[PDB]
Length: 152
Ligand code: HEM
Image 1: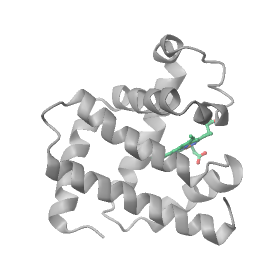
Image 2 (image 1 turned 45 degrees about the vertical axis):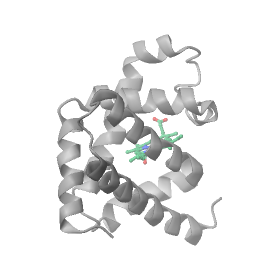
Image 3 (image 1 turned 90 degrees about the vertical axis):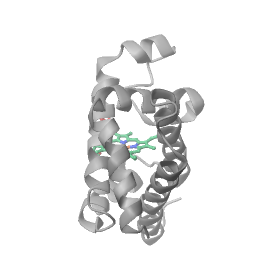
């Protein structure tokens, strides 16, 4: 649960991402894959990437980063009223991709890391607080659907 002022902060931060969605999306995925190499094994289309240079050169990885962040932005713009947008993603991630909730924690922390890396000194304590709460709400509502499905 976020206040209006907290949502305002989230959507202000999100404007930074929307100026360069592919570059942000690329860096989020590279931070996830290099920091948590087990996550790469869930992607049949990325498991061939052995080095970060290959990851950086991969146009398909940047494309998937765009898909991911576009979906997340659509959810965030709902300011918590996201049941219809979140349900299919929870279902695909539990039943088809088999992504444990732990990896959603990993990508959440990776988003924070990338924001500080690309906007140093311009991602303030209030903005980090509100963005963190929004990612927690997203993860928690996914977790409820995972529990319904019995997925661990
Ligand atoms: C911010 C959280 C994330 C968002 C919003 C997101 C969004 C998406 C979307 C929109 C798709 C395509 C449609 C679908 O299959 O449902 C996708 C595919 C996928 N997601 Fe996620 N995702 C997230 C986190 C993750 C994480 C943590 C992993 C793995 C570590 C992951 C693994 C995948 C895989 C395996 C695919 C299929 C790729 C394909 O083969 O083309 N997702 N995701």
